[PDB]
Image (tube, rainbow, N blue to C red):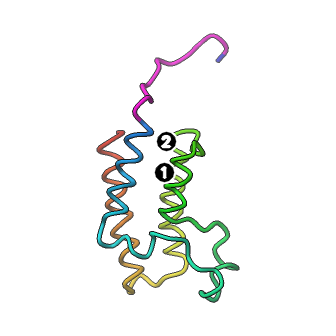
């Protein structure tokens, strides 16, 4: 509350650490469905169904340009990528499986780096 603060958690390395995590996601062999925005002209249904499209290149641009106010807003966009994937893709599909794998990979890196 006013003039009553919890001790200051050091957040000065968060930008660099989110960038490293993002690099590792970008270079994972199952990242291919997620590298670029889904082409809204060429994928029937996507525009109407997926209210907030998100992909690694769009996260990279937002990260690079100061559009994440903190590390939690960064994690929300990464998880949005996988939540979108689950909404549109069957679990038993290459893309569906890719999304499960990447979410697992992300969450471990996130915990090991920050928790």
Q: In this view, does 2 lie above or below 27?
A: above
Q: Give the range drawn in magenta.
A: 2-13
Q: Would you say the residues marked 2 and 1 are in contact, meaning their CB atoms lie under 8 Å apart?
A: yes
Q: Is residue 8 magenta?
A: yes
Residue at the top extreme?
3
Image side of residue 31 versus residue 73, left or right = left
Query: Real-space Cα distance between discs 2 and 1?
Result: 6 Å
Q: Residue at point 31% right, 53% down?
A: 108
Residue 14: within the magenta?
no
Q: What kind of element bears circle 2?
A: helix
Placement of the N terminus among the 4 image quadrants:
top right
- Say which residue appears at 60% left-offset and 45% top-offset: 67
Residue nearest the observer in this picture, 7 or 20: 20
- The residue that label 1 is drawn on is 75
Question: Badge 2, how many Cα within 10 Å: few under 14, some, many 20+?
Answer: some
Q: Residue at x 54, y 39 (%)?
A: 70
Residue at numbered disc 2: 71
As displayed, is residue 27 above or below residue 98? above
């Amino acid at each position: 509350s006013m003039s009553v603060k919890k001790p200051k958690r050091d957040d000065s390395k968060d930008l660099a650490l989110c960038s490293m995590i993002l690099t590792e996601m970008e270079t994972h062999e199952d990242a291919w469905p997620f590298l670029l925005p889904v082409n809204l002209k060429l994928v029937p249904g996507y525009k109407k169904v997926i209210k907030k499209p998100m992909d690694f290149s769009t996260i990279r641009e937002k990260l690079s340009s100061g559009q994440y106010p903190n590390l939690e807003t960064f994690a929300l966009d990464v998880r949005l990528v996988f939540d979108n994937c689950e909404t549109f893709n069957e679990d038993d599909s290459d893309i569906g499986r890719a999304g499960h794998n990447m979410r697992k990979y992300f969450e471990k890196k996130w915990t090991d780096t920050f928790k």
